[PDB]
Length: 86
Ligand SMILES: [Mg+2]
Image (cartoon, rainbow, N blue to C red; front, side, top):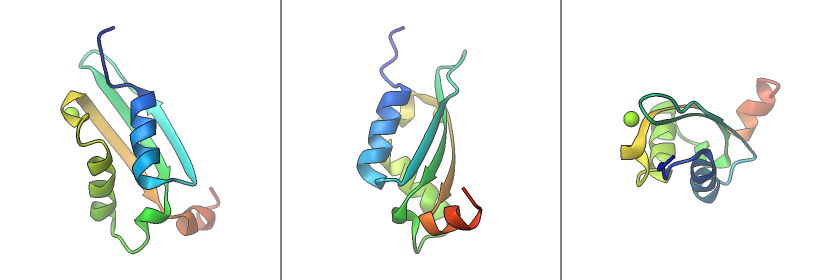
């Protein structure tokens, strides 16, 4: 009720910027507001360390971040995803 950040907006922002091969967003919204966990497989993470990956994801949802209580993520390249056997 009255929240403008949703799992759908998060999904759309991530898809728009990161064009993932695989995305699983968990809606973890609760007492303190909107919150999500994002499992993201994207070629956009190739050539980047984990902090630089996190930066890229946060930059996708920069406009929404002040309205997000918590956001957690796991960022893999499609190569790493295949090597951890998905
Ligand atoms: Mg927050």
